[PDB]
Image (cartoon, rainbow over all chains, first blue to last red; front, side, top):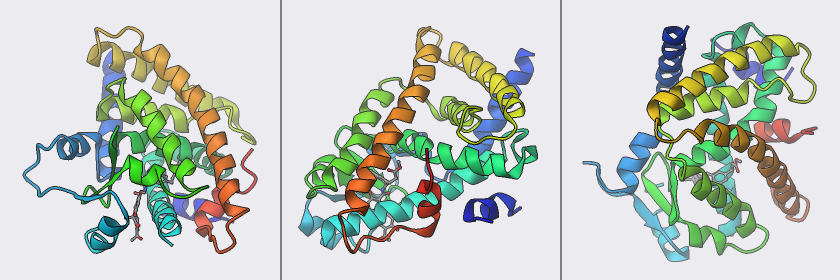
Length: 11
Length: 258
Ligand SMILES: COC(=O)CCc1cc(CNC(=O)c2c(OC)cc(O)c3c2OC2=CC(O)=C(C(C)=O)C(=O)[C@]23C)c2ccccc2c1
């Protein structure tokens, strides 16, 4: 759970 | 094989153009004074900085500006990384690791595109802040700014264009030897193909500079030592400056880096 992970998952 | 390497090169360039608003081509059109757009506002001292606030402690204010742009750049780089064939199919934690260790090396590289010996373009080329104004900022902020120009001068001597840079950046992102990677081979396989695409790009685009590929491989190594020093310079700031606040995204990237 992280900000980088959230940016990576956004289509 | 070669045709497919050129198609890959073009794909990366096209994605690079979509991901990064201010290209080196656009940036050189501004710096050399060849654009129909009005000139960037020049900031060279405290007074000019005050005047140009709407166009774009002082040292702390400029440092925070650098942070905001870095945060924006990390998101641009992330979008670009997701366009590299195979990247989004990697283990998600490895994707995070590649960005964590890659982004600041790429920011050093892409800052060079916006820099000459005299200064740096800011605010999508609407402002131009002089190197000497940034270097003159009180310790420890002046020495945080200067290394980016020192690298830029050496790197820009290679005369890469946006097509070259798209592949160079992709190779850096897909580095299989970043600390803590779980599945190394799939990353190495992607990088091997990107390296082939880069070699061919440089042979065709810079036929009179046989040395360029080998030099760029060395620059990838140099960028690691440059970014380690960058992290050290940030500790001289963060640890000593009491009211200094780091953006959450940057705090995440710097946390447990090496
Ligand atoms: C290895 O990666 C790194 O070292 C990353 C850190 C990093 C980022 C940069 C790039 N800096 C800039 O673009 C910038 C700027 O440069 C001095 C001033 C400035 O005044 C603003 C900038 O951008 C801004 C965003 C804002 O939102 C503002 C607001 C609204 O307050 C600003 O103030 C702006 C306009 C560097 C530029 C030169 C040297 C080192 C750098 C280090």
